[PDB]
Image: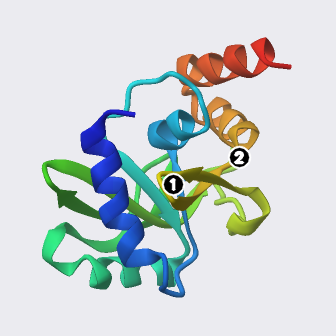
Amino acid sequence: IRPEYLRVLRKIYDRLKNEKVNWVVTGSLSFALQGVPVEVHDIDIQTDEEGAYEIERIFSEFVSKKVRFSSTEKICSHFGELIIDGIKVEIMGDIRKRLEDGTWEDPVDLNKYKRFVETHGMKIPVLSLEYEYQAYLKLGRVEKAETLRKWLNERK
């Protein structure tokens, strides 16, 4: 990953590593940490409902959008944003995808799908690539899903 992302990741990790917060890095940074050669433009952190508000507090001086329940047609979450050294950090708590019948999926057990990567002395929680692949397909993020799939197929 580019050094500026590693540095912001360290700033995040240092504030969360000894706090009782259920968090995982997702999306491009998670893919990159796990070896997928993708460009990273922001940092996405997934957490539970309580976790989102706790992260806001912990990073209070960096908040660009206070956490609040937010929905679109496809997704809802407790959604806030940080900016750290010019890098956007998206905080999404209790993320649910909209189902075909218009209901929301059940709460996602983050611990079920969490993995850990050691980098630069840090143990970073990241989300299962197979989980993200399947979720991206459901959301219609087909090219990103295909990129992950192709990389995973190539390493099987």
Question: Whole-percent x and y of residue 47?
Answer: 53, 69
In terms of secondary structure, where does tag 2 sit?
Answer: loop
Q: First in sequence: mark 2 or mark 1?
A: 1
| Left or right of 14 in this view: 60 | left
Marker count (numbered)? 2
Q: Compare residues 61 and 135 and report the one nearer the observer.
A: 61
Residue 85's mark?
Answer: none
Question: Whole-percent x and y of residue 98?
Answer: 60, 51
Residue projecting furthest to the right: 156
In terms of secondary structure, where does tag 1 sit?
Answer: strand
Say which amino acid is labelled 1: Val
| Left or right of 92 in this view: 137 | right
Q: Compare residues 148 and 3 and report the one nearer the observer.
A: 3
- Per the model, the C-alpha gap separating discs 2 and 1 is 10 Å
- Tell me, yes or no, if residue 79 can be seen here: no
Question: Whole-percent x and y of residue 62?
Answer: 16, 69
Residue 128's mark?
Answer: 2
Q: Quadrant of residue 63?
A: bottom left
- Mark 1, other Cα within 10 Å: few <14 / some 14–19 / many ≥20: many
Which quarter of the rendered picture does the C terminus lie within? top right
| Left or right of 9 in this view: 138 | right
Picture residue at 47% right of the left edge, 64% below the top: 77
Q: Compared to 63, does 84 lie above or below? A: above
Question: Whole-percent x and y of residue 37?
Answer: 51, 21
Residue designated by label 1: 25
Which quarter of the rendered picture does the N terminus lie within? top left
Picture residue at 50% right of the left edge, 41% below the top: 27
Q: Compare residues 8 and 68 and report the one nearer the observer.
A: 8
